[PDB]
Image: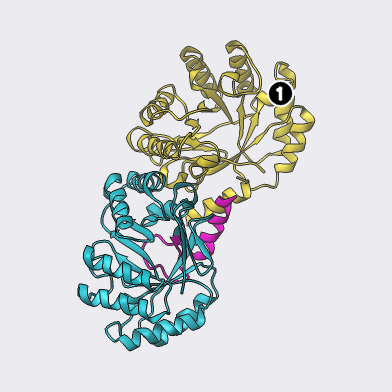
Chain colours: A yellow, B cyan
Amino acid sequence: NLYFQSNAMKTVTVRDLVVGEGAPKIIVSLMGKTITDVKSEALAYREADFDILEWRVDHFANVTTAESVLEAAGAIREIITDKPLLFTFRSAKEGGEQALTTGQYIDLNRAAVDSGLVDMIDLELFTGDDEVKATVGYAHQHNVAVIMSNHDFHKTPAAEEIVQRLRKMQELGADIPKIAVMPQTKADVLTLLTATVEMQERYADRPIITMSMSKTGVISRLAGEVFGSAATFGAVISVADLRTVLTILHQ
Amino acid sequence: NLYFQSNAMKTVTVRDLVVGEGAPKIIVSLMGKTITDVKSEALAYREADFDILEWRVDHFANVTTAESVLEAAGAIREIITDKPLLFTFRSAKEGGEQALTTGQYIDLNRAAVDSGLVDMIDLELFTGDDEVKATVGYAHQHNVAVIMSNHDFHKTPAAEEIVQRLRKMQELGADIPKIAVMPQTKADVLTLLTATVEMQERYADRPIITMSMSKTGVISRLAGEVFGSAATFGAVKKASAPGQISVADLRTVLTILHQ
């Protein structure tokens, strides 16, 4: 593994994929419970037109068995060979499907880094500053990039607060700060876009990923090129529909 | 010669098209110089997928000859028989290709109303209140709906100023208030969307049409369903204003955002 990054165009290059340039990149998630499910999903998505494959490890039943995780990461990499693999255990605290102690979470991410099978890991901003700094360093030592994330599945913080969280991620060494918030009003969607523009403008020296969740916030999944979000998620609105709109907006 | 409107559904229904319900409607502008050009443009437009046909009369060379304007309107109506026809002279003050005195502009719009060939007229917010109220009344008496419009081609006013202009249009009797503004920054695009949401949620009792122009504001032409703009402009071959994308691409995106 070896990735690049530049503060000129504010990009991160993982594989041949330049995150931060051109149209936003599409991330799809594997949410299988067993290795059978994970393999069936990866094969099914192999033909889809997406850019980054995220493995949602919190959906994996054998997450506490080290060899099972390594086995599943290898299985995915065998099927999807030409795309960055992002390893993401979403914590219970931030909406994930299973609970792990801080120690288990950090060791899980360390094992993923050590495997050499994953290009990027997702680390949560509020895990703990000492733990985050240590793990970002460890990932970087092994040429693995870090998407640092934060979520609010029930409300949208003030724009100022969103910007300061994205800034903190940058200060903790995130290669790509990422935040997802839930709108309660239409104005909240615009608040998330405002924060995106303000961060991109005032502080960003690398790509950022932002999203306003739910049908109400779908705009935020399409307008990343103008507003400054480098990636968006879709499932196989759909991945096909997402690429269609992104291509039109790039023209 | 009869349109409907519902204050509660915030809709205006013209020639079976329900503006303000479902996905935003697509408006295309016909911009020919001579009657020959108008006829051939109407035929080319028949091949496209749009909801409302706007005739940009300020592009027509013989606008000062009443007979010529009526002939052109009739030629369009003969080709586009099932879609609403919107009559729009964009004033010189607000970017128009030619200038008319206020009195000439008012008489032009009254003649369009009288013709029975157009379903809607566009009147500019800053034309002159007393004459706009009189013309709105005249249009309504002949069952012609009024889109009232305002443009700022060099900047984006504050959100509250955009809202106030839209409210003033409603006050003047506009069936559909319309505003187009030019962003200088990315934040200006968001300002226009904020004004759209605030107007639609708090003060509107009818459909509104809003847009942030240029490539930078194109998202405002796509996200009307969520934010509250009832229609959007697309280009058949050439844009009538900066930021319009193809009608085909516009419908593709609107359909995706509808579900």
Q: Residue B43: x, y in percent?
A: 51, 81
| Callout 1: chain | A
Q: Is residue A56 above or below residue A80?
A: above
Q: Who's the residue at 60% across and 41% down the image?
A: A234
Q: Is residue A77 visible?
A: yes
Q: Is residue A151 above or below residue B244?
A: above
Q: Who's the residue at 52% across and 27% down the image?
A: A154
**Residue indicated by mark 1:** A70
Q: Amino acid at mark 1?
A: Leu
Q: Is residue B98 visible?
A: no
**Who is closer to the viewer here, B145 or B122?**
B145
The kind of secondary structure element at disc 1 is helix
**Who is closer to the viewer here, B129 or B68?**
B129
Q: Is residue A70 left or right of residue A130?
A: right
- Place residue A143 in its image quadrant: top right
Q: Residue B211: x, y in percent?
A: 38, 55
Q: Quadrant of the N terminus of chain A?
A: top right
Q: Which residues are magenta?
A: B232-259
- Place residue B233 in its image quadrant: bottom left
**Who is closer to the viewer here, B12 or A22?**
B12
Q: Is residue B20 left or right of residue A97?
A: left
